[PDB]
Image: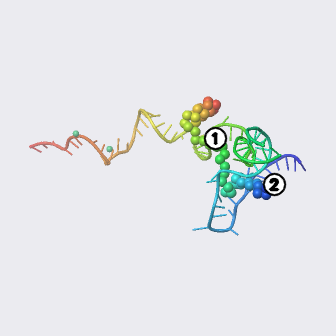
Amino acid sequence: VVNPLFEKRPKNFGIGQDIQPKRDLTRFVKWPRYIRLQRQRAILYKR
RNA sequence: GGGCUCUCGCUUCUGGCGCCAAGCGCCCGGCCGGCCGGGCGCGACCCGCUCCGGGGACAGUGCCAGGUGGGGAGUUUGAC
Ligand SMILES: [Mg+2]
Ligand SMILES: [Mg+2]
């Protein structure tokens, strides 16, 4: 029944091994000046 | 099988290649147990409040006060 051709082909997201995937980067975004403002406004209000 | 600490998370003989996902699970869409065409998530751990670091309540900026200042400006440099 099974085809010998269907090999399972894992990828190595190691250092240098293979190129890395497009994962979520919201924490490091260069936000516009209005957003960065209102956020660190609320933070000052806390501090 | 259990507690504790640290490390790692897989690359050092060579002038090479390396993108646009494999696989699995779970869903169902048309046709007729089989065919054609679709979707999500694991695979690629979870949560957060400042992009990362270094300084830092001092440099610094604004206003007064003393000083220094032919680098520069203005003027003078007697009479018989
Ligand atoms: Mg002067
Ligand atoms: Mg004059």
Residue B22 position in % (x across, y down):
73, 52
Q: Residue at x 64, y 31 (%)?
A: A46
Q: Residue at x 60, y 33 (%)?
A: A39
Quarter of the rendering occupied by the N terminus of chain A: bottom right
| Foreground of the two, B31 or B68 | B31
Report the image quarter containing ligand 2. top left
Q: Which mark is residue A2?
A: 2
Q: Residues within 10 Å of mark 1 (few under 14, many from 20)?
A: few
| Foreground of the two, A20 or A1 | A1
Mark 1 belongs to which subunit? A
Q: Is residue A44 visible?
A: no
Quarter of the rendering occupied by the C terminus of chain A: top right
Q: Which mark is residue A26?
A: 1
| Foreground of the two, A3 or A12 | A3
- Mark 2, secondary structure of its residue: loop
Judge if badges 2 and 1 mark residues of a common chain.
Answer: yes
- Mark 1, secondary structure of its residue: helix
Residue B74 position in % (x across, y down):
24, 40
Q: Is residue A13 visible?
A: yes
Q: Residue at x 62, y 33 (%)?
A: A43
Residue A41 position in % (x across, y down):
59, 32
Inspect the image, locate mark 2, and give the three-letter code of the amino acid beneath it: Val
Mark 2 belongs to which subunit? A
Q: Residue at x 60, y 34 (%)?
A: A40
- Identify the residue at the far top of this view: A45
Picture layout, residue A12 above or below residue B51? below
Q: Residues within 10 Å of mark 2 (few under 14, many from 20)?
A: few
- The earlier-in-sequence mark between 2 and 1 is 2
Inspect the image, locate mark 1, and give the three-letter code of the amino acid beneath it: Thr
Tag 2 and tag 1, C-beta contact below 8 Å: no
Residue B53 position in % (x across, y down):
61, 47
Q: Which mark is residue A37?
A: none
